[PDB]
Amino acid sequence: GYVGNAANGQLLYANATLDCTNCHGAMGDGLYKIDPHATVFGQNNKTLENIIAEDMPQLNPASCGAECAADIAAYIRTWA
Amino acid sequence: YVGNAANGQLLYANATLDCTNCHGAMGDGLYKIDPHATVFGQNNKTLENIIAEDMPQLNPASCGAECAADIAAYIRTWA
Amino acid sequence: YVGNAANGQLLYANATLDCTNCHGAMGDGLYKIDPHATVFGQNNKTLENIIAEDMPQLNPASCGAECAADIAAYIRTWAG
Ligand code: HEC
Ligand code: HEC
Ligand code: HEC
Ligand SMILES: [Cl-]
Ligand SMILES: [Cl-]
Ligand code: NA
Ligand code: NA
Ligand code: NA
């Protein structure tokens, strides 16, 4: 399995093109909230990695796939 | 002088130098930085010298040779 | 209690505390922090005590004695 790299995720989350921070804030307390402790996300109870891979960023979800998502997820866990 | 990347990470994020506003957190902002390239600009400068001589644009003298080297050392990690 | 600079780095960058919004990543933001100084403000407080008692402005109590000591230990490293 891939194992997310939090250091990569720090930079990927802040990436100007992905633009996560514009919608979610620096640590998920912006316009749309992210709970960094939750293990299931959305109506389909996806993992953090899969919700990011499949659905984020909204502009173009395919621009952050599985490894990107795994890295970002590892970084998001540190928010708590 | 040999760049210190821990220093470089803070200097790149420095609020006065403000590199991130123009270049993003990892060089994918409005103006791109390619962390793989070894020559930069029309005069084929090193990463260190392009930063020292030309950046930030507001006042290039605010990040001189040592600052540039530390920031360059950090930017390579984006590869 | 002896501050843990590694943890200080994490706390300083935490968006709930939001120290970087006002002070910058290395104390060169809107409000400066001098990492060499040993007295701060008009009651000549220690670095730890100014943070514990007064920062962040949104809610001083969100960063107590331990938090302040860790962050202070990190701030000293900016001198390098
Ligand atoms: C322009 C809008 C927009 C952008 C850009 C965007 N998001 Fe979202 N995101 C949303 C909205 C809207 C939701 C659903 C509301 C919510 O739960 O926060 C959401 C939900 C999420 C959730 C589920 C949150 C929860 O607690 O249920 C995660 C995780 C998330 N986004 C991460 C990211 C990451 C990582 C990026 C980019 C790297 C990103 N988002 C980019 C708008 C955005
Ligand atoms: C307000 C604008 C602005 C600020 C601030 C700024 N730059 Fe730049 N930078 C540019 C522009 C414009 C170019 C040339 C176009 C390009 O290469 O993206 C450039 C070019 C560069 C290049 C060469 C990239 C290339 O491929 O040719 C590097 C490296 C760079 N800047 C680093 C920095 C660093 C390090 C800082 C601050 C610590 C900084 N810049 C601050 C606008 C800025
Ligand atoms: C939204 C504003 C704001 C936030 C958030 C904030 N500060 Fe401050 N801080 C100030 C202001 C204003 C001063 C006093 C004015 C000055 O020093 O110019 C100050 C003073 C300080 C001083 C004394 C510096 C001196 O010599 O004058 C330290 C140290 C400091 N803050 C650290 C922190 C730390 C650590 C955090 C959060 C973890 C924090 N601050 C959060 C606004 C902020
Ligand atoms: Cl970026
Ligand atoms: Cl700064
Ligand atoms: Na995605
Ligand atoms: Na310069
Ligand atoms: Na406090």
Image (cartoon, coloured by chain):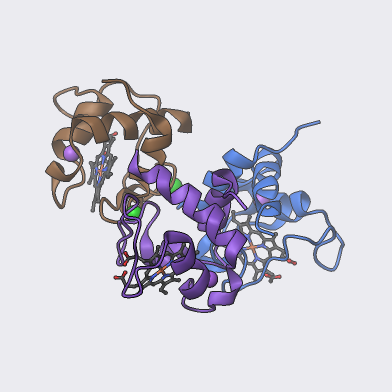
Chain colours: A blue, B brown, C purple
Q: Quadrant of ligand 2?
A: top left
- Residue B7 position in % (x across, y down): 37, 37
Is C63 or B28 nearer to us in this picture? Answer: C63
Identified at 62% across, 72% down, the residue is: A32
Image-based side of C24 in relation to A10, left or right: left
**Residue at the spot x=41%, y=28% of the render?**
B76
Q: Is residue B18 left or right of residue A61?
A: left
Q: Quadrant of the C terminus of chain C?
A: top left
Q: How many marks?
A: 0
Vertical placement of C77 versus C41: above or below?
A: above
Asked if residue B28 can be seen in this view, the reply is no
Residue C43 in percent (x, y) is at 35, 74
**In terms of depth relative to the viewer, which is nearer, A79 or B20?**
A79
User: Viewed as shown, does residue C64 lie left or right of B8?
Assistant: right
Instruction: Estimate the x, y position of residue C41 in percent, counting from the top left.
Output: 33, 71
* Residue furthest bottom as drawn: C58
Q: Residue at x 27, y 27 (%)?
A: B47
Q: Is residue A69 above or below residue A20?
A: above
Instruction: Identify the image quadrant of residue B50.
Output: top left
Question: Quadrant location of residue A5?
Answer: top right
Residue C77 visible to the viewer: yes
Work out whether B41 lies above or below C73.
above
Q: Quick one: C20 or A51, which is closer to the camera? A: C20
